[PDB]
Image (cartoon, rainbow over all chains, first blue to last red; front, side, top):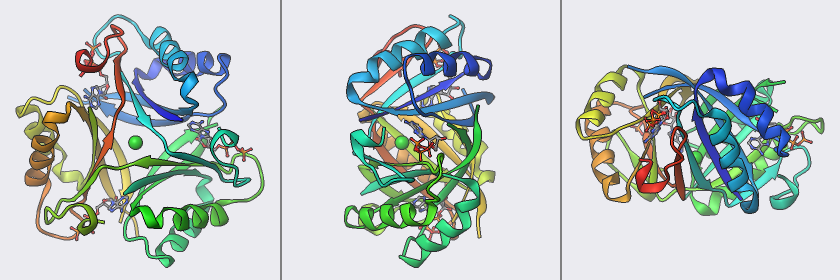
Length: 95
Length: 95
Length: 95
Ligand SMILES: Nc1ncnc2c1ncn2[C@@H]1O[C@H](COP(=O)(O)OP(=O)(O)OP(=O)(O)O)[C@@H](O)[C@H]1O
Ligand SMILES: Nc1ncnc2c1ncn2[C@@H]1O[C@H](COP(=O)(O)OP(=O)(O)OP(=O)(O)O)[C@@H](O)[C@H]1O
Ligand SMILES: Nc1ncnc2c1ncn2[C@@H]1O[C@H](COP(=O)(O)OP(=O)(O)OP(=O)(O)O)[C@@H](O)[C@H]1O
Ligand SMILES: [Cl-]
């Protein structure tokens, strides 16, 4: 499993969220942040199975891209376990 | 060492914080976030020794759980080093 | 590549940002958070090449340190890939 953390322009959030839901993303966490003299940005975090990482990365790139400076970056971070709070399910059963 | 990132319902924050302090957690970072059409959630991050991860996970699950949809998830992420800013202490000496 | 996540006192943000830019940091993401009964803190995230991690850690420690309790902590988290949204560049080409 991997955590995909993407920092994008705020106005791109609904489009990116819609695109991710469309390819099957079940959950996502959004944080208001600032970055680069700081400009507002939106952080999106999604945790997915290893075999789904590339599709998510390409979907975020294609949907959040404007071609202008400041479009943002995506970081792929390893996740060793995932636990669903409601049920105690883990790993594959919790994504 | 591992970072435990948990996304929980906002009203569960004081209970979860109290439960974590009770089992010995020295520090925690809380961020206001939104998730799933987005609903407010609270992100808690705690970095702990490998041998303390399971106790923290079980404590968050038991305290944040309501049995209803939206209870949240917990992600376990590897941390290669930890540094205490005040002293420069690292690793085991900084947790 | 590694993600350096530092939680610091809010008033230290401009100094730390200036110090990081000075040693060559191209980008950084800042989040308003609370921590420890919670006090406001600022989270800074920077993703850098492995050979630049120590310089960044020392720069944050030296600039954010006051010697008083609450100065904060720095976590070093592995990053498996980085993607520049504007161009699709990855890894070394995206930092
Ligand atoms: N190295 C980094 N570490 C942490 N956060 C970063 C880093 N680089 C970028 N970010 C985050 O991504 C946001 C958008 O950055 P940005 O789109 O400018 O990337 P870039 O390297 O400048 O490529 P571009 O030429 O398209 O601007 C930054 O404001 C910051 O929030
Ligand atoms: N895959 C994910 N990636 C990133 N964040 C997630 C992911 N899944 C859940 N979250 C975060 O956890 C929050 C709560 O999710 P939630 O409790 O609905 O998990 P779930 O999979 O729906 O299980 P449940 O059936 O109990 O709802 C979401 O709003 C989001 O902020
Ligand atoms: N173990 C931890 N897990 C997650 N976040 C932490 C942890 N420890 C500290 N933090 C974050 O760092 C912030 C500042 O902590 P702090 O400076 O008090 O570290 P410390 O261990 O108490 O060392 P000091 O004696 O200098 O206070 C905390 O408020 C919290 O936001
Ligand atoms: Cl992380």
